[PDB]
Image 1: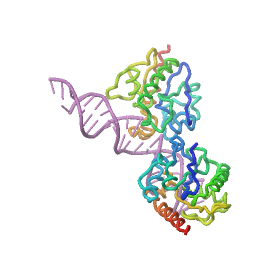
Image 2: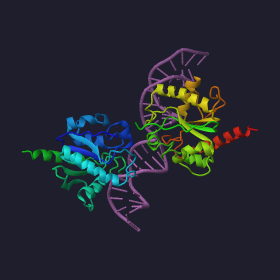
Image 3: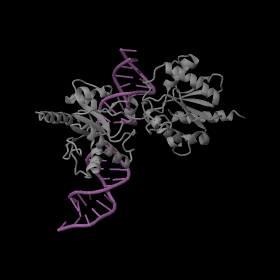
Image 4: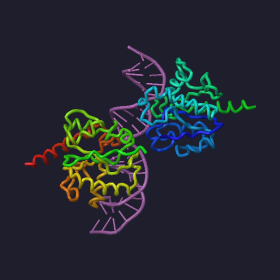
Length: 182
Length: 185
DNA sequence: CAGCTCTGTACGTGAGCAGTGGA
DNA sequence: CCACTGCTCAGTACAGAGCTGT
């Protein structure tokens, strides 16, 4: 359905559950603009000006950010997924990331990482909180960073004004990681 | 490609429901007026047009059991009606009229005023003054098919905010069809 | 301004949630 | 697996400019 915007030597990679109906139709990542992504990407200072799904193909070149998902199959709809599917997805994911080895793998929303941990590391995270996670991407110096879902279905994150902090903190981490090249 | 919702249509049909075009969900689900939000299936039941509650899965049984069909003005799928070309509508109504001239349903039901406002301006060349829901004067060219306008079953419409608000016109729809079947003797 | 023709606001639910906190 | 706090998302009357006319 929706294409992977991915390059080599990338700062951040955003990682969704799977492309939404809109996404799939629009042919661009995190459209909406119910999905709070682009507003946050702006507000955070990760983007120079305000952007949108149409600017999505420019992100890695200009702001060093990639895009992808656990499962490429499009649906509503996360409750529409399964399990078998996820496990096979993480497998397909891990590989792609073992190929492009970005600096930071960002998980859009706890759900996706919950699974990913239990499947990639086989660890059931007790009281998971957002931010850097201990373990790295298998056989890679890519760290796992967990962000609250950009999806406009999160009420802990009712506005994009509510969930901007983590993006600021995300930016910082990239910076910190850039420093360690000296 | 998502891509297209099929026409459930037969010969000698009481009602044909006519949407703008198929929504993202509709197109993905492969069934008419899925949701929610669509008050259609609730109303279809609540009105008395269906024996029991139904849903998008039952869409292909409707002509057989309840003599109801389905189609839309424009086939292309989008969000999204504000996403449609003025020219696309014109080509739709043209295509539609045809369909109706072929299947000759008793009544063509128009889901929502917008779709008829255009259809009139394009099939009859008349921009209706202060349009109201219900029966319309003119029949489908070369047919005995009446035109009846319902408020959009969709749920972007605040005049019919609940599904309870839109039930009337389905009751009235039922009556009309019964009247029309009555005269069959 | 009586209508009018035109692009454009702005508006009410019930899902379906992703959270956080409880049975 | 719920109850819940808040968010979204899925056409159509109405607003003003901007007309010709008692």
